[PDB]
Image (cartoon, grey):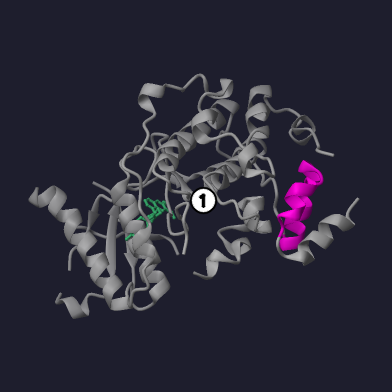
């Protein structure tokens, strides 16, 4: 059926060209197997041009020897990290178009009660024809949660893009998490360099404070871990986005400012971001769908043995083929 050529990320390999992902020893570790089942069900639930899609899943040898899962996707030229940090063009109009598509993908995603929680340029794929697709859904969760990650929210996802609520454990974990990350991504496109490149937990809070200023007392009281509160209080106003990005566009910084706020409830939504004057060029409500029905994460909260999860994953592969080949 397919012929491999070269390995890309590490396992994904190039191979009509396609990308093929090996998930080796998929059923050997509970965490890895649970993540594979979550990704399967999320990607099958979504049908949207700005969200990665599975083209094919290679079938099962006898069942007991079924160890690895191969997943076929359409090959994407690059990702937004490789584009941002290179000699490629990235004018304001590039920034405007890439931001639109991310936000278009998020409106759909957020309407199904799914929070990505791991948006960074490297997870935003871009093909030869400039379609941007959100990938890598292993960190995604709903509004309700059961996991070590219930506590320890400061270890959720990637440090340079992590929202203050996770860092500080503010007990208000919503789709607003992704809009922080978008803010960082947006800022990073405008300057071609990371906005908040923290070295460790403490330096990451510094660098956010050096732009956003001191957080409010009501935010500080909602920090549960007392040791972090003491550090914040030991330090002696916001820096205007104009002086952070000197040559930048006016409409862009307005929108950026509505994303990078300490308080989750103060952040603009994906839907409302798409109504901002900066994205008027591309904004069409009739072409920017919601996702119905919503995604249920109940299956993830179940404490399953590796073998039950294996059975679950194999049923999602069977159902994938039945919905197209059979029916
Ligand atoms: C030249 O650059 C690249 C092109 C690329 N083209 C296409 N797809 C990729 C990767 C994107 C991220 N990704 C997933 O989101 C994903 C999808 C399905 C999965 O299976 C399961 F879990 F549902 F079972 C697991 C992971 C894996 C595929 C690509 C990755 C590239 O660089 C790293």
Magenta residues, start to end: 199-223
Q: Position of residue 157 (x, y in %)?
A: 55, 59
Q: Position of residue 228 (x, y in %)?
A: 77, 62
Q: Residue furthest right?
A: 236
Residue 295 on the magenta segment: no
Q: Residue at x 21, y 79 (%)?
A: 65
Whether 109 is drawn above or below 256: the answer is below
To which quarter of the image does residue 140 belong? bottom left
- Circle 1 residue: 122
Whether 323 is drawn above or below 256: the answer is below
To which quarter of the image does residue 232 belong? bottom right
Which is more toward the observer, 282 or 225?
225
Would you say residue 14 is visible in this rendering? no
Q: Residue furthest left?
A: 326
- The residue carrying mark 1 has its beta carbon less than 8 Å from ligand 1: yes
Ligand 1 quarter of the rendering: bottom left
Q: Residues within 10 Å of mark 1 (few under 14, many from 20)?
A: some
């Amino acid at each position: 059926e397919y012929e491999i050529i070269e390995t890309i990320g590490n396992v994904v390999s190039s191979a009509q060209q396609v990308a093929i992902k090996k998930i080796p020893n998929a059923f050997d570790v509970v965490t890895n197997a649970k993540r594979t089942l979550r990704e399967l069900k999320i990607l099958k639930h979504f049908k949207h041009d700005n969200i990665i899609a599975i083209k094919d899943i290679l079938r099962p040898v006898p069942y007991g020897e079924f160890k690895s899962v191969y997943v076929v996707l359409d090959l994407m030229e690059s990702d937004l990290h490789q584009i941002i940090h290179s000699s490629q063009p990235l004018t304001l109009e590039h920034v405007r178009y890439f931001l639109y598509q991310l936000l278009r993908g998020l409106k759909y995603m957020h309407s199904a009660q799914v929070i990505h929680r791991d948006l960074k340029p490297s997870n935003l794929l871009v093909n030869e024809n400039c379609e941007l697709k959100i990938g890598d859904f292993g960190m995604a969760r709903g509004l309700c949660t059961s996991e070590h990650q219930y506590f320890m929210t400061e270890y959720v996802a990637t440090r340079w893009y992590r929202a203050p609520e996770l860092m500080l454990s503010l007990h208000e974990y919503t789709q607003a998490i992704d809009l922080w990350s978008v803010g960082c991504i947006f800022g990073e496109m405008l300057a071609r360099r990371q906005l908040f490149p923290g070295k460790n937990y403490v330096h990451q809070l510094q660098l956010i404070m050096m732009v956003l200023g001191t957080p409010s007392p009501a935010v500080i009281q909602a920090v549960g871990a007392e040791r972090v509160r003491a550090y914040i209080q030991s330090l002696p106003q916001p820096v205007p986005w104009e002086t952070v990005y000197p040559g930048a566009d006016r409409q862009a910084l307005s929108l950026l400012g509505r994303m990078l706020r300490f308080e989750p409830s103060a952040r603009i939504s994906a839907a409302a971001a798409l109504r901002h004057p900066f994205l008027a060029k591309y904004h069409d409500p009739d072409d920017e769908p919601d996702c119905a029905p919503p995604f249920d994460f109940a299956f993830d909260r179940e404490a399953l043995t590796r073998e039950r999860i294996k059975e679950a994953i194999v049923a999602e592969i069977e159902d994938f083929h039945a919905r197209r080949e059979g029916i």
